[PDB]
Image (tube, coloured by chain):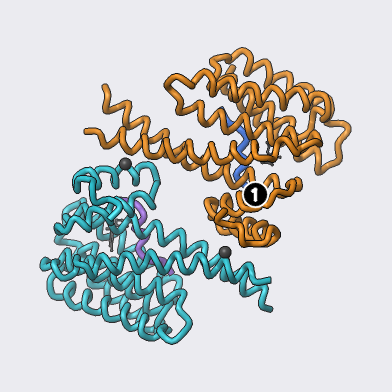
Chain colours: A purple, B blue, C cyan, D orange
Amino acid sequence: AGSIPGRRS
Amino acid sequence: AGSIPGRRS
Amino acid sequence: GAMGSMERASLIQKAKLAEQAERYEDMAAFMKGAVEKGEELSCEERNLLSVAYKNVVGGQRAAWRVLSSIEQKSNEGPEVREYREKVETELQGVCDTVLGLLDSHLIKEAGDAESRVFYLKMKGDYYRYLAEVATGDDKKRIIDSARSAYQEAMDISKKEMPPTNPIRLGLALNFSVFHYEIANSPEEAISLAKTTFDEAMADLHTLSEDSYKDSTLIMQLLRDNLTLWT
Amino acid sequence: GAMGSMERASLIQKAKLAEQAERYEDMAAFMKGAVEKGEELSCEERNLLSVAYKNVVGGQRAAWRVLSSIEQKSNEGPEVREYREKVETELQGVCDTVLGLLDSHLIKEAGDAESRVFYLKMKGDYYRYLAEVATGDDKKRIIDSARSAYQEAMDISKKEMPPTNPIRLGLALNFSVFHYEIANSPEEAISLAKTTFDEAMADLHTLSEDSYKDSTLIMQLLRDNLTLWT
Ligand SMILES: *Cc1ccc(C(=O)N2CCC(C#N)CC2)cc1
Ligand SMILES: *Cc1ccc(C(=O)N2CCC(C#N)CC2)cc1
Ligand SMILES: [Cl-]
Ligand SMILES: [Cl-]
């Protein structure tokens, strides 16, 4: 299950 | 130019 | 703290440089210093804070899972357990640091829906990460702390944001992962992801091309989980 | 040091776990503690030490290059220079730490060709990394320190190791990169890589299938550079 990748911004 | 990758052992 | 002598704007600028250099520990320390200046964070600044700590704890979680897997295979010297405990303690420390920033004093000063939902989603996420490694007497309280933060964020997002809002969608995505992975409620997880996806689909017609791209990107993450879960 | 109370064997075991968890800073600290126990390192242990610090300084070098590139574009506030200097100082500290371990006392206790060449190659590499960021009054001395270490390693390897020995081949590879990238001697770099490749090719017939695979893997790295340089 994937959460928000949210690794790039 | 590549040196020894040497990142895995 | 360690960053007390640096200008707020310099901390923000260096956080952006650290992201470009993939130096996420530095990025998190710079953004921690920016938060501790005491001013509210802009939309962009909130993203920098979140990206920094998500990367840091993401690496810790991946390491913890490798070591927990090795540890379980061995229980089928003390070193594997000791090193897993070391990584676990470091992860808990980072989660506590983020939760401390939200509690002192990001959340209480956040009055707009976009900022308040963003911070409460973060609070749910970092309690979820604590729950992933929790075993003892506080596992249930940690789980309920995650649930309570996610639930408050959901209530606000449903009242104040359109169904396609990327923060609303990502909140529902992560709350659904909480239901599936932490709360042992896969039916709740599937129902939340489905209802979230369907209500966003029906709102896409209102969006510009760029907003459409932002929303459909997160909707695909919901769809990916539904495909895995059904 | 920080690892003085842990058993040597536990430090080695945890270094291997850290590698599996991709926790290279931990791996390097564990192997630093193992070295400081004062006993010589086995072949496997030398590889753990080298892999750990190569990964750590590799990330620092990649970050330094990103920031140096941004800094040069800006010179066509002080923050980019300040943060590049911070990363640079951290990289120099890691290089100094590795060079300190080689000098106290890995190299002086290394009597076998395989160990002595391995450590001298390391010494050349970490002076080469210092040379990559050096500008001021010591850039020439740092360069000569790299050259001297590589040269001593080459002299021993030519006398004591077959032309297909992977350490001999990797030493020649990195010395050729030193010639090309640091010493402004591309013809020396090309000549070294060519002669190294050709002498290894002529010795492949002596090898087992597994040794053949080990040697041809490094020979391809020499070939890749020759293709880039000619
Ligand atoms: C909590 C949260 C929700 C949504 C976003 C967001 O819009 N993005 C991050 C992930 C990226 C992908 N894939 C797209 C942009 C951030 C945080
Ligand atoms: C200095 C040095 C030389 C050779 C090796 C080595 O044999 N390996 C590391 C790189 C890897 C690849 N590609 C193959 C194995 C290590 C260190
Ligand atoms: Cl440990
Ligand atoms: Cl800085």
Residue appearing at x 80%, y 27% in the figure: D163
Q: Is residue D104 above or below residue C169?
A: above
Q: Amino acid at mark 1?
A: Glu
Closer-to-camera residue (C36/C166): C36
Q: Nearer the viewer, residue B6 or C208?
A: B6
Q: Is residue C12 visible to us here?
A: no
Give the answer, above or below, for where D129 lies relative to C91: above
From the viewer's perspective, is A8 left or right of D92? left
Residue C123: tell me if it is visible. Answer: yes
> So how many labels did they put on this image?
1
Callout 1: chain:
D
Give the image location of residue D3, x and y in percent.
Answer: 59, 57
Question: Which residue is at 50% across, 65% downward?
Answer: C87
Quadrant (top left/top right/bottom left/bottom right) for the C terminus of chain C: bottom left
Query: Residue under circle 1?
Result: D36
Location of residue D123 with respect to C172 vertically, above or below: above
Res D118 quadrant in image: top right
Q: Residues within 10 Å of mark 1 (few under 14, many from 20)?
A: some
Q: Please tell me whether mark 1 sits on a helix, a strand or a loop.
A: helix
Q: Residue at x 35, y 63 (%)?
A: A4
- What residue appears at the point 54 percent right and 55 percent down from the top-left corner? D26
Location of ligand 1 given as a quarter of the image:
bottom left
